[PDB]
Image: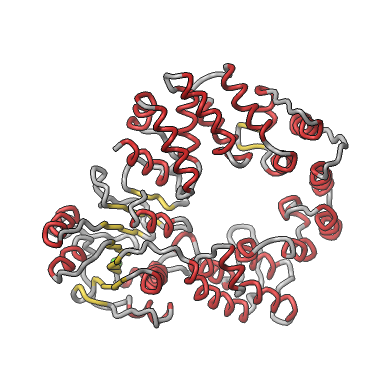
Amino acid sequence: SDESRLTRFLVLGVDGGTFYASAQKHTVQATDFVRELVQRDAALALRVTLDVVRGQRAPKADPALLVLALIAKTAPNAADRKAAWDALPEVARTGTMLLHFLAFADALGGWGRLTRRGVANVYETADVDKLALWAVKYKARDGWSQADALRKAHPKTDDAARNAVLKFMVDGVLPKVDSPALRVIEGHLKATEAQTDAAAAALMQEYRLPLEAVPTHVRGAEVYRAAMQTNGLTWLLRNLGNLGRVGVLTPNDSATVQAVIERLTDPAALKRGRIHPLDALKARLVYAQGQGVRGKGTWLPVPRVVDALEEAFTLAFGNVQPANTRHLLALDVSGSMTCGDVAGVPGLTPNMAAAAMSLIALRTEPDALTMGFAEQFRPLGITPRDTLESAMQKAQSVSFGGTDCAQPILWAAQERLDVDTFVVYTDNETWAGQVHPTVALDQYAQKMGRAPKLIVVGLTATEFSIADPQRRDMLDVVGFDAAAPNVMTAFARGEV
Ligand SMILES: [Ca+2]
């Protein structure tokens, strides 16, 4: 079905059953099916695309932006090209997304009337606050800048304030209406000219300015101190190291320490911020290193903060959106599972990641059973009562067998176990058995009267292929990242 095949491309960013959960290239490129579909039925291409954007299941806007460009620029009909343009303001939510859309479109046609108007409509529809934000935060994206687009599109609004910010976005010259939209602009201007951690701090204090506005050279204690009070939990999670470094968060400075602990374990803030347990696990591991990636400095991890992150992990389970399907999780339990940094997270071993995901399933899905490719294929005996640490150990066995992704499915049919979703967790070592998982899945359907799905996760994989591109019941997840769990859940629910 065109609808289903296009939706899959829109979510995964590929025209097959593979999610590159990444930190690699895999930039979305339009395949033949996608172009052919846009010519054949641009109207449904567009309806499908809006459905996906609104449904918000796509980890990335990229594929929807590309598809939208294709329709807008190359759809045979004028009503379709026009409808695509009319949707641009919705789909290109941020300044970056608009510049990204233009990078896709510029390879499909020049600046005809539809294009000038369509781009102009984006700026003319945005309020003075969104415009000001774009003016300071989304100035450029590689080749394309807001200035470029504005010179080609020439937007004009009814109100002088917005025209003033549009003018500023082109010529960088500061006016002075006010609408405190200019305020944030003036603030960002002065911020670039700081030289001192204190003036910078005093500046975002005066001007409600983001930590972004502060030159890397001057972001000291007062700058980070200031940033905390003005950001949510997600920010806080990825900034613990930056706080240990700039001398704000230290083992002998209890007031800030307690205040961080309270935010990290605030159930209401966890829920509203939609913190996934892996988000908390990543923050803990990153923070506990006391040293960052290239060119970062060091810091002294505060133990009780590390502790609070362990609590945030447990509390976050309550906010996971379940597939609501019966899962059988088959874990690779061999020694190499203890090696590697999944998703570039220092210390996040495939074994740790798989144990975390097992606990999640056990605690949130209608049913879940965990098996392992051990001496023989057997239950690991992990339960919702386990900790991350005890589950990790149950998922390690000195004697192991090949990681055969067909085998959990063959086993379940043999045991007449009702399973909706099979999930295999490995590092990068799928091993082919005598029966392919496709045959396995067919045999299960034939014996049990239901067609289940299979997800194979290569937690540190760069490339493998198990999922049949011609089937819909299979998904390969290559690598891992923060978007992977939601994609897997969406897939299991039949939405991908
Ligand atoms: Ca292995």
Residue 51 vs residue 311: left or right? left
Residue at left offset 29%, top offset 38%: 1
Asked if 218 appears above or below 393 in the picture, the reply is above
Q: Residue furthest right?
A: 176
**Is any atom of residue 339 visible in this view?**
no
Task: Please state the total of marks drawn on the protein image.
Answer: 0
Asked if 153 appears above or below 172 in the picture, the reply is above
Residue 342 lies, in percent from the top left, at 44, 62
Of residues 301 and 365, the one nearer the viewer is 365
Of residues 130 and 244, the one nearer the viewer is 130
Of residues 373 and 308, the one nearer the viewer is 308
Residue 176 lies, in percent from the top left, at 88, 37
Q: Where is residue 263, by image quadrant?
A: bottom right
Q: Where is residue 274, by image quadrant?
A: bottom right
Asked if 473 appears above or below 252 in the picture, the reply is above
For ligand 1, which image quadrant applies? Answer: bottom left
Residue 117 vs residue 131: left or right? left
Residue 357 lies, in percent from the top left, at 39, 68
Asked if 474 appears above or below 118 in the picture, the reply is below
Residue 224 vs residue 43: left or right? right
Look at the image and name its color scheme. Answer: secondary structure
Residue at left offset 38%, top offset 42%: 7
Residue at left offset 29%, top offset 63%: 424
**Is any atom of residue 168 visible in this view?**
yes
Of residues 14 and 122, the one nearer the viewer is 122
Residue 262 lies, in percent from the top left, at 66, 76
Residue at left offset 40%, top offset 46%: 12
